[PDB]
Length: 46
Length: 46
DNA sequence: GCATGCATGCGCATGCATGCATGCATGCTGCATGCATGCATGCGCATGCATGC
DNA sequence: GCATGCATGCGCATGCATGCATGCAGCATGCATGCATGCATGCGCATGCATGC
Image 1 (tube, rainbow over the protein chains, first blue to last red):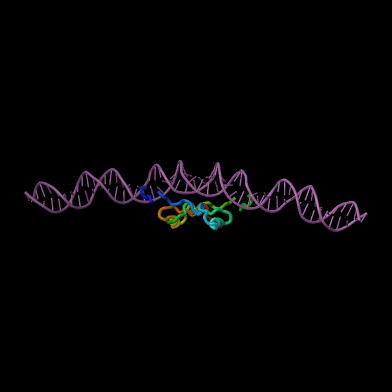
Image 2: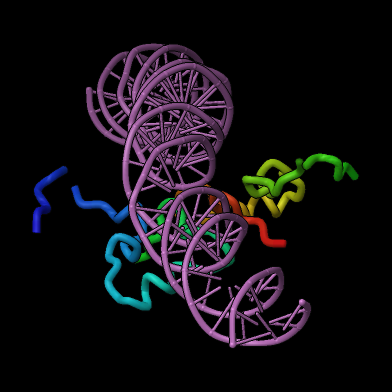
């Protein structure tokens, strides 16, 4: 609601990790032997 | 052929870019409007 | 029947596989700079035509 | 016939959309330490039994 600047941008990291919301979600975030889920440098599609 | 150390490791970046081998391969490496193909931090599966 | 030594559980102390956050440094990468290049533009000058006389 | 003025093409500088590499920095990820925790070790000590005399 602020279009006067000429700014919002797309998030740089996946928000699933910082919103540890569900009890099974933080469990789906793990696995693949021993490592941490890494989505990538900028993974958001419109 | 050297197993005495206790070392080879998996490549950290995709080798498709440094081996600009085919004439259509360097063309498949582009697109998606304006950006550079980014495979990720470590993308090799055995 | 009395004396004896063994095997059975208590009652200490120590080490050890799991597991997770923090500060420092690594390693990449997106950004700002400089530049080559070739197409278009905005321009003044020389020629050939149309309109008088 | 002759003198004149306008449209058309030639010649000359300039700007500007594309495009790509390099030095520097900003930026997030992986690593080293440091510790908390609960389990298992193994180790002397007390009790109840089986054997000898």
